[PDB]
Amino acid sequence: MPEEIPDVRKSVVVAASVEHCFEVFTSRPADWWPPSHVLVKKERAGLAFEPFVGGRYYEWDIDGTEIVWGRILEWDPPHRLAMTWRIDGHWQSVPDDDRASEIEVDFVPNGSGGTRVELAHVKLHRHGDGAWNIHKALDGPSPGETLARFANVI
Ligand SMILES: CC[C@](C)(O)c1cc(=O)c2c(C)cc3c(c2o1)C(=O)c1c(O)cccc1C3=O
């Protein structure tokens, strides 16, 4: 959980379908952020999700109004898609991010309810200045990595 976010690439297979992987993201990504063992500093309130290229996802915080914490780049019909993240230093959305980075993500459907996902983020440090702090509100726990909470619920 370093304050700086250098380029890192990790991937794992979870029991889920690529369409399902995104159904959860566009269905209720905040509802599972907080499982129980780990608590979130801010309570998620609502979430807006629409499909498209250069897309955007919005999260509602009881203390934070509606804002965009991520972005998209393009969707590949099969099961592959690249996405960009749109966020500001104070969790605010802006017409364009000078410190924006590109992320490459690919999904592969595996029968028996299994999906392989490869998510890699590079040049993220472009935001620096407490960059992880921004992610910290989004919850960046180490003991309960993202694969632990979101994969188990899926
Ligand atoms: C501490 C948060 C974590 C898990 O290290 C993290 C941080 C990550 O940077 C991260 C990266 C690099 C890749 C994945 C994932 C990544 O998530 C990831 O969570 C993931 C997943 O939950 C299910 C399928 C695939 C993935 C990933 O490919």
Image (cartoon, rainbow, N blue to C red):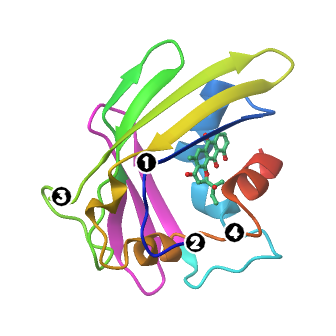
Please give the range of residues in magenta.
45-69
Answer with mark 2 or mark 3, whichever residue precedes in sequence: 2
Q: In this view, does 66 lie to the left or right of 137?
A: left
User: Neighbour class for label 4 at 10 Å: few (<14), some, many (≥20)?
Assistant: few
Q: Residue 17 appears at what percent x and percent y? A: 70, 26
87 is higher (above) or lower (below) than 102 = below
Q: Do the residues labelled 1 and 4 touch (CB within 8 Å)?
A: no
The quadrant holding residue 84 is: top left
Judge by depth and name the residue closer to the eye, 121 or 111: 121
The residue to which callout 4 is attached is 142
The quadrant holding residue 142 is: bottom right
Q: Residue 38 appears at what percent x and percent y? A: 75, 76
Of marks 2 and 3, the one in the foreground: 2
What type is the residue that disc 2 sits on? Met
Q: Residue 124 appears at what percent x and percent y? A: 35, 56
Q: Residue 97 carries which label?
A: 3
Label 1, secondary structure: give it.
strand
Label 2, secondary structure: give it.
loop
98 is higher (above) or lower (below) than 23 = below
Q: In which quarter of the image is the C terminus?
A: top right
Residue appearing at x 43%, y 50% in the figure: 7
The residue to which callout 2 is attached is 1
Answer with mark 1 or mark 4, whichever residue precedes in sequence: 1
Residue 66: in magenta span: yes
The residue to which callout 1 is attached is 49
Q: In which quarter of the image is the N terminus?
A: bottom right
Q: Residue 35 carries which label?
A: none
